[PDB]
Image (cartoon, rainbow, N blue to C red):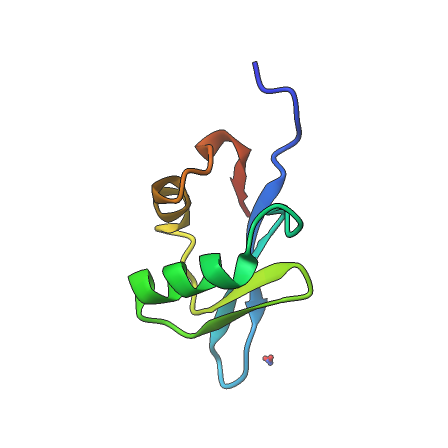
Length: 83
Ligand SMILES: O=N[O-]
């Protein structure tokens, strides 16, 4: 059984003009290149976004697809909490 918390958190923050953004927090920024992971997810979703301050930010609400997309990048789906 899993011996850690649901350490990759995915949640929504407000953007302007009635839009929203998806935040992915908890990917180890020391070990992995969050800029690169952001670029990959941006390309898969054709959306804007950035990596900053230890988090990835994506334009729009991508909670519907984020577990599949992070699993395409090898992340364990049990570590991912979509909030
Ligand atoms: O972020 N302004 O909704």
